[PDB]
């Protein structure tokens, strides 16, 4: 089966780790078990095809430029995550996309825009604003909640579909 190297990027606090843990372990913070050490290699079936997701989370190294570049060289596809209640995290998406294009030396890198924490009421980034940004980038946009699991599989699966294109 094919393996897909997926990298989760985005500002500190947007929920990169929470999203990955929902995909891998199927729960949120209340069910966090510190005795369990999960694997970020997961076998899944996407559109009837079985494959392996190999996930890298940049959490803790967001501001570590040399390591950011290593993630971007390695990754086949990128989840570009912001939080819908953090406009600065949305603005940071520009810088992540730019750096990915530069490290890859390409303008057509598999990428999905993810607006996380859509379960929260206090939104500061409109769904239409994120849709327009993704449109300008030529990439999909998905709203997610690591808390309710809304859109979590869809975000990762859609990224795999982008790589498959
Ligand atoms: N309500 C809500 N909280 C979230 C969601 N995703 C993450 N969080 C919370 O946001 C905080 C930061 O999440 P984390 O994954 O550690 O952020 P990061 O690794 O810095 O990107 C954590 O305390 C999470 O509980 C979400 O979808 N909904």
Image (tube, rainbow, N blue to C red):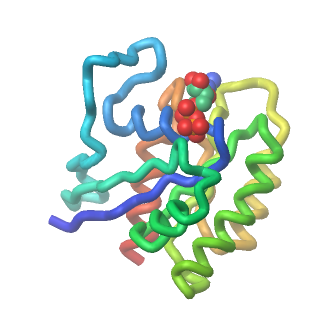
In depth, the one of 91 and 145 nearer the eye is: 91
- Residue 93 in view, yes or no: yes
Q: Position of residue 3 (x, y in %)?
A: 24, 64
Q: Is 89 left, or right, of 160 in this rendering? A: right
Q: Residue furthest top?
A: 30
* Residue in the image at 40% along x and 52% along y: 56
Residue 164 position (above or below residue 12): below
Rendering coords of residue 58 (x, y %):
50, 50
- The image position of residue 145, as x and y in percent, is 57, 33
Residue name at image x 45 percent, y 48 percent: 57
Q: Residue at x 69, y 40 (%)?
A: 83
Ligand 1 position by quadrant: top right
- Can you name the residue that lies furthest to the left here? 1
Q: Using the image, determine if residue 144 lies above or below residue 162.
A: above
Q: Residue placed farthest to the bottom in the image?
A: 105
Which residue appears at 61% of the width and 81% of the height? 102
In the image, residue 126 sits, relative to residue 131, either above or below, namely: above
Quadrant of the image containing the C terminus: bottom left
Q: Is residue 121 left or right of residue 153?
A: right
Q: Position of residue 157 (x, y in %)?
A: 40, 54
Quarter of the rendering containing residue 80: bottom right
Q: Quick check: 121 left or right of 141?
A: right
Residue 158 quadrant: bottom left
């Amino acid at each position: 089966m094919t393996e897909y190297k997926l990298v989760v990027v985005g500002a500190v606090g947007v929920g990169k780790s929470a999203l990955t843990i929902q995909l891998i372990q199927n729960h949120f913070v209340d069910e966090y078990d510190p005795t369990i050490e999960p694997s970020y290699r997961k076998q899944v079936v996407i559109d009837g095809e079985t494959c392996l997701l190999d996930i890298l989370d940049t959490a803790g190294q967001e501001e570590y430029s040399a390591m950011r570049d290593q993630y971007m060289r390695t990754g086949e596809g990128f989840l570009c995550v912001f939080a819908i209640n953090n406009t600065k995290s949305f603005e940071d998406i520009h810088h992540y996309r730019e750096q990915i294009k530069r490290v890859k030396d390409s303008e057509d890198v598999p990428m999905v825009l993810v607006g996380n924490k859509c379960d929260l009421p206090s939104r500061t980034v409109d769904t239409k604003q994120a849709q327009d940004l993704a449109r300008s980038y030529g990439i999909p946009f998905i709203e997610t909640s690591a808390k309710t699991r809304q859109g979590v599989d869809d975000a990762f699966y859609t990224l795999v579909r982008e790589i498959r294109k």
